[PDB]
Length: 212
Length: 224
Ligand SMILES: [Cl-]
Ligand SMILES: [Cl-]
Ligand SMILES: [Cl-]
Ligand SMILES: [Cl-]
Ligand SMILES: [Cl-]
Image 1 (cartoon, chains in turn brown, blue):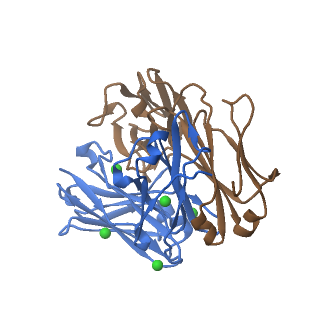
Image 2 (cartoon, protein in one colour; image 1 turned 90 degrees about the vertical axis):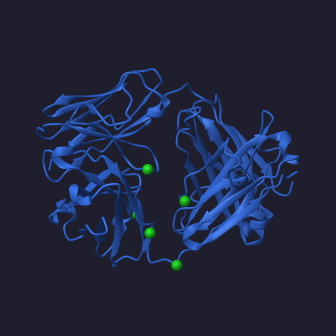
Image 3 (cartoon, rainbow over the protein chains, first blue to last red; image 1 turned 180 degrees about the vertical axis):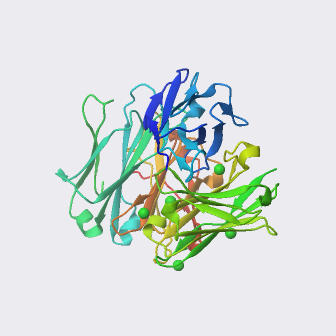
């Protein structure tokens, strides 16, 4: 089976920049093919027979290569080009795809805005208390959230997730949920999430006191 | 116009079998090759195999021999993928896609919308929906964040809209997280003008189709 190795796995570019990514085959192939895929949707044909653009693909895209080395280029990046690009070969069975190059949007550092939400009274009636910490519109993606209850760090009782890059402003947002029993929630006073991010000169803590 | 219409989401216990289907319109599948492609959560595309509906000839990636069986019926213009003795490794999105071979320059030129398969014996479970109320702790620059916590459901997905789709700007609906209980939770937040809190109603509309759960939750300000 012909292994297709795509480099880089992940890269980031500003609108207007030239972008090239490569696809290397373990043995020679006649033509290379490419597909674009965005989150939660089907892949789209993008380039076929190495250099022919599929219908609807704008002229800033091109494809090149021969033998074992192929590449896809964007002459001048647009925000809408942020996506994963897969190469694929038809010269040998089984058909194989590369593992993808994820093209992300580069922008300037942006510090998160940090907000905290106590559990609802509704949820408290049910015996559980979820506290939510929101980090809105930051860049780059890496961010550290630390939950403290009466100033004691919390380990192993939270879950967090991060949106896809926002295509309007190229930032990320992050939501973290601390989940305690109602018993443990009612036995402590101060609930705080502490955020570390490269956009902040020192960590930011948002907190509230239960019942106030 | 060419369309590939795939069958709906499947939740199936491990060890059982499942049949996915892809109904073509705007062309005859006998003139094409009908392929299936697998994409596991957060992973790349994997080719499973294909059938030539003109003669029934199939080819499979050896990885999927015995797991996958591909058939096609030309009278209904439908291709099928049957998977046997399901495991958690079969949980994935399955795409059907066509190729026209040599005379159509080979590439996968049309793709179905995908079918999600979740392999689990668990019952479906609808979410609880709790407000994330706006307050002085969620305000910045004359705006206020509020939201809904959509907790403890199975399987994916839920959809969240705000004010029945009239509110779309400044919404962030976060990816679901898997909890240690084995159930999912997600939050959806929206940032709005602080001035609007006393004068604009905000409702999150939550749908969990697997359990037939629809919840509308009005999110009200909290004066701490
Ligand atoms: Cl799609
Ligand atoms: Cl269906
Ligand atoms: Cl899995
Ligand atoms: Cl059920
Ligand atoms: Cl979901």
